[PDB]
Image (cartoon, rainbow over all chains, first blue to last red; front, side, top):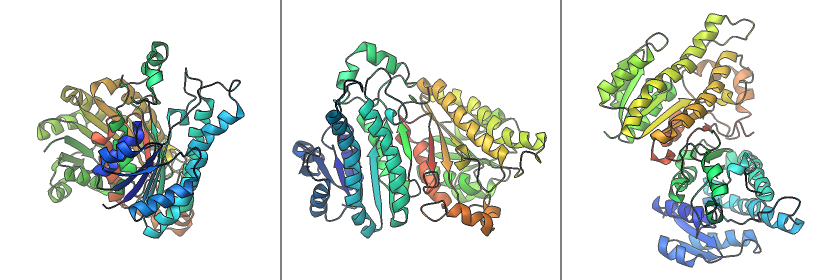
Length: 239
Length: 239
């Protein structure tokens, strides 16, 4: 395969859809997650079992390099969250969310960049949220909101630093998507109704619809597109 | 051809590159401009001679419908500007810039929407600028800045209104691109140097690089992407 890609959180939800879209583009893909074997076998990707809440990120990148024979694309779609308001949230919980979403994003990108630079072409795709621009509405998710907003700053910073190395860095911000990660949200009218009423398209996205844009940001289409957030939200933020 | 597209300002610069990219996607394209015949013949599109600074916009849309047998995509890339500071600018000049960039955007979209709605699928692509987010730096372009920023509001408004009609509306914001429209800017060190120093990628874009993203926003990739600005600027805004 052409481009070599590593997708964390690639066995479920959005990550899985992105991995599938990249395989469809002819990329050699490695899927990292706690239990990536089923997804890897089904999608035709390389499985890299890992617990990114504990395992050294650069170690995962090394494994990806060894498994793929190079590294051009990094998509950090790993998911996790502690849905509690700030007054209830413990520092440990705050750190758990910020570590996986933000610190690991930095560590993975830092480790992957030299390989992309050597190849003279790279794409880093961080995953944001509508909470990169708002506070989540009826849902108490301060840590998640902070982390997903922080990613926009990291995106701009790395895009600036690595622009001359052939690397493009962007933040894909999906809106409300039908996935297991959002399963608890959709199964409650008091929350689903008010949120959906603000989506002009009147429906939540299918993971594959989000992946179409992720693929663009991981390809030649993004040659002159870097340091930006791209929201794919059915019109939610515009409402 | 599949999708039917109308591209204004499609015989030169960014518009021409977008028209070419759409033809490459298998779309039946109509190019509108003062003298679109050479471009239409070269690219394999339908020429629609028109002076959008004077001719009724809905009349152009009608001609496009007749020439293409339908209408799914509208790209308003027509260009014009009066580079004078606010204290020097006359109301007539202010209106000239706002009319072509903004009023005509509204009139063209308003006329095209019913046809897209009937087809159950549509894409409206307005063209912004880095001045949709800033004031142009060393260049005195208040009218242009105002118009290109206004387009973001129009984009959100129309995206919201037409979401359930199958229409997606977005604003492609190109950075500094090598075109004849920007020819006077590039031929002056005192202006080119300070601007380029703020582009992380260290170079201006080729029209075709911008068109790659325009094509995405005029295709199925943008199914769940609406009411947004997408900046393709080599990292300029992020710097």
